[PDB]
Image (cartoon, rainbow, N blue to C red; front, side, top):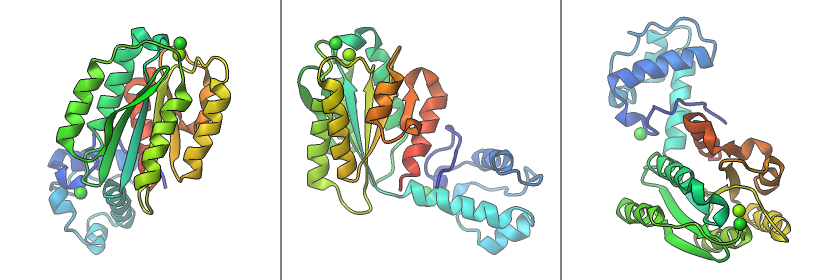
Length: 257
Ligand SMILES: [Cl-]
Ligand SMILES: [Cl-]
Ligand SMILES: [Mg+2]
């Protein structure tokens, strides 16, 4: 159910400009090996595009119209799905020179998930874990949540199982059917002592609650270590992957609905 939508394109198509519709068309054509689509085939914005019928799509693109209609529908269906995103953020001394890297990632990601049925929660952890921002879809509270993350000063050990625990406890209380709970751990992978075991054990609880566990490594990280925390190796993304990993995880999350 994956749609490799370009990063630029807003999550919701009703905000697409006339130029976004052209760019969607150019992308769809290379992504899906479609026959040449005239860039003048849909001369309208997203609002207008949502009013065309499938048969209109066929009139306008006899070769690819039905496919483009369904492609839109999937895009729209994932843009309206419910998501609980829980960011588990490493604040240990291992990442002191990389707090920049973690924060700008969390912010880029939060500024994309803006639909009314998307809530976010910010959790930090070092030796202990703390909830900076309780799960909420309130943009105003989320902004203060971001402003608090900027002042985080990284210190301590890497007790990542404490961080996942605070995600779990929130999911227990408001996790629901048709509410894809997602966990995004931004860490460096340097786990000492029993933390690897407790982490792999605690990520299973997340999977036992219906949540999907994504791992995002910062700077130089242990690839194998994260692979054991995330659901699959396909759910591990390097933060240094820039706009390319950032797109990848978005569409991976969106296709969880
Ligand atoms: Cl929309
Ligand atoms: Cl450490
Ligand atoms: Mg560390």
